Amino acid sequence: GSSGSSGYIKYFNDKTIDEELERDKRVTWIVEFFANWSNDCQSFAPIYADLSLKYNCTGLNFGKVDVGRYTDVSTRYKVSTSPLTKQLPTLILFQGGKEAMRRPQIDKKGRAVSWTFSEENVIREFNLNELSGPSSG
């Protein structure tokens, strides 16, 4: 009865990513935009997995959309897919069908601010522990 899940994430297409976020608006959704050629992402591979599983319950959901290949998405989400830029990996918080916040933040000119990528920083910045309530039972 829904027992036996390990490191499982819900992927989204370039088109569905919309319909889905449209039927779960009221519900918060966190999609991680990463590229197949993103090495720095490998270090997060396990990090994200651990996080999701934690906040993987009734209320908050986790997703992943490889932009490195889905040029149709990145372009729509103004997510540069260059090996030089710092828009990969990337995290975006959607609340009620609205981009609550994203990181790293984009400067006025149009450059990704050098932000550290860690669980402590993510949970805090995004305030996950607060979003999907505290961990403590």
Image (spheres, rainbow, N blue to C red):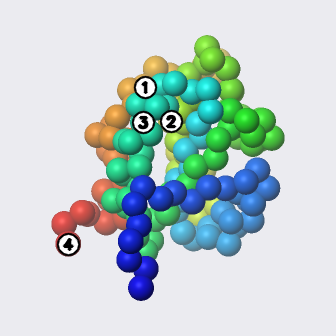
User: Which residue is nearer to you in this view: 97 or 36?
Assistant: 36
Q: Residue at x 74, y 65 (%)?
A: 19
Q: Secondary structure at mark 1?
A: loop
Residue on which the image places disc 3: 44
Residue on which the image places disc 4: 137
Residue on which the image places disc 1: 115
Front disc: 3 or 1: 3
Q: Is 56 on the left-hand or right-hand side of 103?
A: left
Q: Pointer 3 and pointer 1: residues touching (CB < 8 Å)?
A: no
Kind of residue at badge 4: Gly
- The answer to whether 22 is drawn above or below residue 77 in the figure is below
Q: Pointer 2 and pointer 3: residues touching (CB < 8 Å)?
A: no
Nearest to N terminus: mark 4 or mark 1: 1
Q: Residue 132: x percent and y percent?
A: 37, 64
Kind of residue at badge 3: Phe
Residue on which the image places disc 2: 103
CA–CA distance in space, label 2 to label 3:
14 Å
Q: Secondary structure at mark 4?
A: loop
Front disc: 4 or 1: 4
CA–CA distance in space, label 4 to label 1:
31 Å
Label 2 crowd (10 A; few <14 / some 14-19 / many >=20): many
CA–CA distance in space, label 4 to label 2:
29 Å
Q: Is residue 127 something one can see in this rendering? A: no
